[PDB]
Image 1: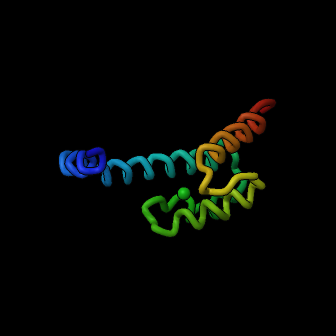
Image 2: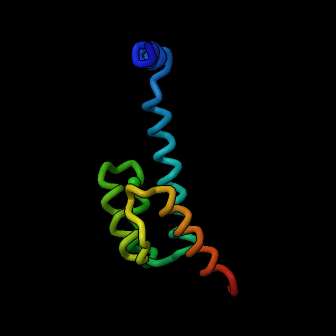
Length: 95
Ligand SMILES: [Cl-]
């Protein structure tokens, strides 16, 4: 059975820590984007975005997407990333 085999697979490998690592890397990427490319906030005001191991990090990201007028929400992560990269590129082009 597919579901029974999935429970066996989960015992072979618990993906939780790797999903957590991916979240961290994703958050670090957002932080680098804000710090070096979007630069929407004052540097003093990026502290909450920077605190990537916080369980409240998504709340801050939601405020960030609002603050830069991103048309996507956090739940649409792939679209938010692409949009923020597009914004970063347009901000970067022409010094
Ligand atoms: Cl998030």
